[PDB]
Structure formats: C-alpha cells, structure tokens
Amino acid sequence: APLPTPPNFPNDIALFQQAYQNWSKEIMLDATWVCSPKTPQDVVRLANWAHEHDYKIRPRGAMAGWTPLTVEKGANVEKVILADTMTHLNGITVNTGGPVATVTAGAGASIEAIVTELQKHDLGWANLPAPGVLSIGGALAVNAHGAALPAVGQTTLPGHTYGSLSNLVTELTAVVWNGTTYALETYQRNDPRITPLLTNLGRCFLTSVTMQAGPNFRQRCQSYTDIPWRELFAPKGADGRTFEKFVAESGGAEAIWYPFTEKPWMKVWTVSGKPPQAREVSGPYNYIFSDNLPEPITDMIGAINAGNPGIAPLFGPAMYEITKLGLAATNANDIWGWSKDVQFYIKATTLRLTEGGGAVVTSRANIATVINDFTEWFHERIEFYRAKGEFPLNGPVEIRCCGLDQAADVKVPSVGPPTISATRPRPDHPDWDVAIWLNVLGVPGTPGMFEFYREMEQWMRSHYNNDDATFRPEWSKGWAFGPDPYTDNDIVTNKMRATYIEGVPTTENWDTARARYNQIDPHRVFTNGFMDKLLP
Ligand SMILES: Cc1cc2nc3c(=O)[nH]c(=O)nc-3n(C[C@H](O)[C@H](O)[C@H](O)COP(=O)(O)OP(=O)(O)OC[C@H]3O[C@@H](n4cnc5c(N)ncnc54)[C@H](O)[C@@H]3O)c2cc1C
Ligand SMILES: C[As](C)(=O)[O-]
Ligand SMILES: C[As](C)(=O)[O-]
Ligand SMILES: [Mn+2]
Ligand SMILES: [Mn+2]
C-alpha cells in the first residue's frame, strides 16, 4: 500500500518506498519514505523542507542496530523521511600535517572503508568495533567501541584512544538552526558546543567528521577454548589462566560463553615481527565458522523458533563445538596481521540476535571482581530457571573491556569528552579508567528472555552502585526493559537522565546536552516519539 505523497518535495531528490526492520526484526515497518542526499547541502534542503511541512528527518546508516531512534515499532511514519547517508555522503580524505594525522569522512562512510584508507598511509585506530559495516555517523551516535586496552607497560601511541570512536573527533559538520533557517555549521573540538554532538543518538544530523589517527600496528589474535569458565572468570588474584592476567599481559580480550557450556571461547589480542607460531592474514573476518552456519545448527534454531526453547542446553554445546572444530580446521587459533584485519571479525551475515546487559565503569584493578560477580550471578540464574523447566537464555554471555574517553588521548585543543557517552570519565572517580561490557545475547522471540533482561538490568543497577563501580546501559543494545526493550517508562524518562547527571557538573551533563540539541533543532525535525521521551 502506497504512503501519502509528500507535499512539494524537492524535485531533484528522488524518493522511494522501502520496508524498515531493526537487526532482530523486533521493529518491522512495511513502508517508509527513503531518499539518498547527494551532498551535505541536500540534507539542508531536506531539513528546511521538513520544517515547512511538519515532517521529521532521520539519518539512515547501515541499519546494523536495535534501538527505536530511527523508527519506532508500530509508528505512523506518513510524515517521516529517512535520509540514507551511505550511498553518496561517503567521501574519505587523509590529512597528514599537524599536531596529529587525521581523516575526514562523510557520515555515511563505513568504518571499514575509513580504516582501509588509513592503512594505505600507515595509520590506524586502536579500539575498533567488531563489525566493519557500520557507518561512522551511526558508530559515533552510540560511542562505538571495541575490546582494546593497552597491556601493562604499553604506552598509548599519539593519536590513538582506548575509549570510544567519539573521543577521536577533531571537528564535525552538522545541519543546524541558525535563527532563521537550517544551514551547515562546523565545530572544532575546542568549542564548548561540540561535546553533546560527539555522541548524539541521532538527535543531530552529522554530514561529515574529522578524526585523529595514530600509527598503524601489527597485532596477534589468539583463541582459547580449553579454559573452564570458573578458571577464566575467577576472583581477584586467582591461580591459572584468568581474564585479568590476559588483560595485564596483552591488553585486548573478549570472552564468548555459550549457554550450558563448560568452556568459553576466549580471544586475546597482543600488539607486536610476526610470532613464529601465528598465521599471517591479509584481510578481516577470519572466523569462517561464525559467518556461516551448517544444517544441524540451523535446524536447532528453526526448532527453537517453532516453539521448542528446551533445545537451549543442546544448542549451547553445539555452538561451542562448531567454534572449537572450526578454529582448528581453518588454523585460526593464532593469527596475526594489521589492526583492522584482526579486530574486524563480525560480518553482516552473522546470526541475528538481541542483547541485554551493559557497561560497568570502574578501575582497572577491579576487573576480576566485576566479571566474577556477573558470571557467578548469571550461572546461578540460568540453572535456577532450568530447574523450573524454563529456558529464557539460548545465546552467549559476551564480555570485553576497553578504556574511557581520556583527555590525554586527544592531541588537538579540546574542551573535553563526549557529554553523554557511556565511556565518559567520571570526575568524582579519577581512578575509574575502564569500561567493562557485560552482554547477554539471545534468539529473538524467546519466551521469558526480555523478562530476564529486565531482571538483569535491575540487578546490575543495584549491584554496581558504589565507590568502586557504577553501571551504564550500552546505548546500542537493549535497555529500559519493561519487559520489552525501550518500554520501561521510568527508565526512559527518569533513570537515563539520572545516570548522566550523576557525578558530573551541572555545566556539562544530560541537561546541558538536551539544551544544546534543542538550540540546534528547536523545531524537533531530527526526532521521533521515542526521542521525545528520552531527550525532551
Ligand atoms: C551484530 C552487530 C555487532 C555489533 N558490534 C558492535 C561492537 O563491536 N561495538 C560497538 O560499539 N557497537 C557494535 N554494534 C552496535 C552498532 O555500533 C550500533 O548499532 C550503531 O549505531 C549502528 O550504526 P549504523 O551505521 O548501522 O547506523 P543505523 O542503525 O542506521 O543508526 C544507528 C544510530 O545512529 C544514528 N545515526 C546514523 N547516522 C547518523 C548521522 N549521519 N548523524 C547523526 N546520527 C546518525 C541514528 O539516528 C541511530 O541513533 C553492533 C551491532 C550489530 C548489529
Ligand atoms: C560484539 As557485540 C556483544 O557488540 O554483538
Ligand atoms: C550509591 As552512589 C553515591 O556510589 O552512586
Ligand atoms: Mn549511583
Ligand atoms: Mn573503594
């Protein structure tokens, strides 16, 4: 069924109708209006047109995400235009000459494309998200990050950050109200106005960004599937092959622990000179068994989807075995290459899942305790539900750490970190210097799963709430589980604000960010109904 034709739409911007679905298909719309602006000036034309006709505009990147910040479930989108940035707003230029090398990218450029160009100039980023498909605008919007820390004794090379990609921004350009009309405006990192824009949840429309780059580096990625979970996730100072020891020795680490299994898949990244035992790779996405699944597994997933959640204790071990056998068969337990080739490992063809948990901001010395508390709690819960015949949990626990948006990493003049990034340092706790990402993944539609994600969100908020650690939702994942994600009204309208006014000055907090967003867009062109609840 055709949507109403928009009134007097700019004649040279082609409009087409497409479906929209979020990653888990928990948001599904049969029809939306879409266009692909050719230049930043065309986004300006779209915004002024929208203002004049009471339409809304949303930037559309790779759609590799879950939140309702583009379109909401069940929403009337008759007066909404989605502006695909990836078709044309994708230019990339490396700039070598200043206090630091930089790269200027259209907001629709993919992060893989950006860092591929950086590699040609012997440059790179230290803390990359796992999927390269992401648009840079979409990555910045949520403080996108990887699993990287420096090893003990490792210095941060000039230009690099172990925080979010949002910490690397030296300048950006956005569509902004000037008092009479929307126009392009450019902000430098030393401008107080920029900090809410560095992580903006799509409340602002970025057309281009410039980001610092450091030197590229070679990196090893070793996999282990032979460490029992209680050994890996042990209390502080324990014997054996512990998570904290890997972080000390190597810096970068991520564990994937399938449900009802004994041994995680642990990945450890070490900066280098190739180790004799490692296999050199020349491209990303080196885990072929995880981008493509065979028939016995897809049959289990099919049977789960058909109403058999009791397959979970068979499915977890089956996924572990595909991983163990696949790593061995393809000789991928010990690989080495440029940063991007070992840090990009999730292809867009990966199994569609939905996520809970979030971030714990704390001191580096407290990593073992945070992880041990979470994994012991999780294990007790999953076994508790199994004993009652209930299987709310059929995907892995995933755990990784990175750094925060440290001022020391920024090599241009700067007014500070992103205002509302989950990676923003806490001024009241200068010793808090890591973010621990504690995620749980599950098959969409699983009975009891969102109830459990609510149970977990409540537990994390209450448990990680003291002088040693605090909890922040991961913007890009599920949160405000009511029990469905993004539906607990108290969390959306009260507790997210509370999180982002805690421990920070009233001159640079959640309310500062809201004020800036409304100054830039008082007509609320760059909003939807969910945005209006979260950021009034
Ligand atoms: C399987 C998978 C793995 C992932 N792994 C990681 C991970 O390793 N680390 C990590 O940090 N994240 C990860 N993500 C989450 C991902 O970073 C976010 O979902 C991201 O926002 C998606 O970017 P996108 O380009 O697909 O944008 P979209 O999904 O199209 O949009 C996402 C958000 O960005 C905003 N946005 C897009 N373009 C602009 C723009 N030009 N200006 C202003 N706002 C804009 C939108 O309004 C929206 O809020 C993963 C996601 C998936 C699906
Ligand atoms: C690598 As992940 C927990 O953001 O899907
Ligand atoms: C309970 As408190 C003051 O550590 O946020
Ligand atoms: Mn608190
Ligand atoms: Mn203490």
Image (cartoon, helix red, strand yellow):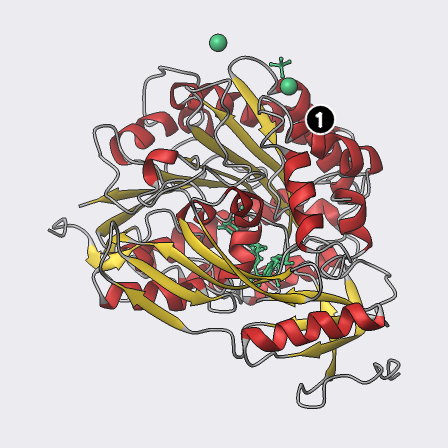
Q: Is residue 370 left or right of residue 286?
A: right
Dot 1 beta carbon under 8 Å from ligand 2:
no
- 330 or 106, which lies in front? 106
- Quadrant in which ligand 4 is drawn: top right
- 451 or 37, which lies in front? 37
Residue 207 at x, y percent in the picture: 54, 66
- 391 or 461, which lies in front? 461
Number of numbered labels in the structure image: 1
Quadrant showing the C terminus: top right
Furthest-front residue in view? 180
Evaluate whether residue 383 shows in this view.
no
Q: Is residue 524 left or right of residue 102?
A: right
Within 10 Å of the Cα at label 1, are there few (<14), some (14-19), or many (20+) other Cα atoms? Answer: few
Q: Secondary structure at mark 1?
A: helix
Evaluate whether residue 522 shows in this view.
yes
Residue 383 at x, y percent in the picture: 66, 28
- Vertical placement of residue 361 versus 268, above or below: above
Q: Amino acid at mark 1?
A: Phe
The residue that mark 1 highlights is 384
Residue 359 at x, y percent in the picture: 55, 34
Residue located 30% across and 54% down the image: 213
Q: Quadrant of residue 210?
A: bottom left
Residue located 74% across and 58% down the image: 305
- 246 or 165, which lies in front? 165
Furthest-bottom residue in view? 11
Quadrant showing the N terminus: bottom right
- Vertical placement of residue 274 versus 77, above or below: above
- Vertical placement of residue 3 versus 233, above or below: below
Residue 424 at x, y percent in the picture: 50, 34
